[PDB]
Every structure is written in structure tokens, then in C-alpha cells.
Length: 129
Ligand SMILES: [Cl-]
Ligand SMILES: [Cl-]
Image 1 (spheres, rainbow, N blue to C red):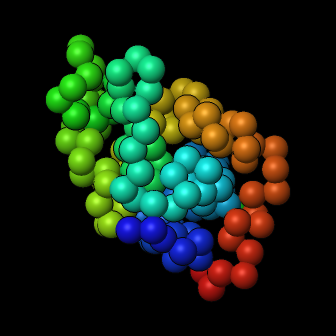
Image 2: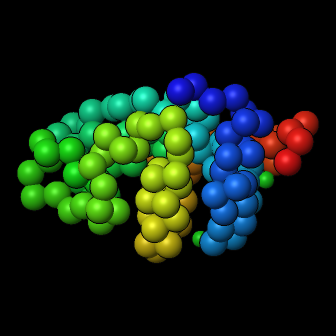
């Protein structure tokens, strides 16, 4: 499913992301924009043989099991395929754990490079939240 911007903001608000660990909702919408273009089915293979999955591009080295990433952790205890669902619950639950881990949202390269220090509120502007 390819979400709308305000639709995504709304589903994220409902799953507790607005202000989770101090990151306003605009940050998470922005991250999703640039990580996956709001598409829950997005996959990107990394050079280390790991794969990023879903709306927030959660990585198979650490966070989810995809069966083809040698000696990987499954820190979110999910098959990575569960991250590609139209229901964003599993992605949101795994992300809350990632962002608690110490790097905060710096764990997402697109956020660090494209959202951090920008006016992230723009991404929720005009949405009935
Ligand atoms: Cl915001
Ligand atoms: Cl932080």
C-alpha cells in the first residue's frame, strides 16, 4: 500500500509516534517519505547482503529475520515480510525499539540526510490530525 501523506501521519499518530522519544510526527512522516516514498512494499538490498523492508526500511542485519542474512539478529522478533503489510503496526513497533537504541533517528540515513534540521512540521501541515 502506497499511503497518502496525511493518511500516514494519522495512522502514525494512532500508533503512538507523535513525540515518541522526543521526535514530533513530522520527523516520522518525513523519514517515511524519503526511506520508502510511503510505500509499505518497498525493499532495498544493501551491499552487505542485508535487506531493508517497508515504510521505514527496517534492516535485516539487526531487526527482522528474512532467512538470507547470515548471523543476523532478529531484535524485533518478526519475519521481515511482516514489515511490508498495509497495516503499519509491526513497522511502528519495531521502529519504537530502534529509536530507543541510542542513535535515535540517526539510524535512518534518509532522515539524518534529508529531514534532520529541516522544517519537519511541513510534512504534517494541512492534515486533520
Ligand atoms: Cl512535526
Ligand atoms: Cl534522540
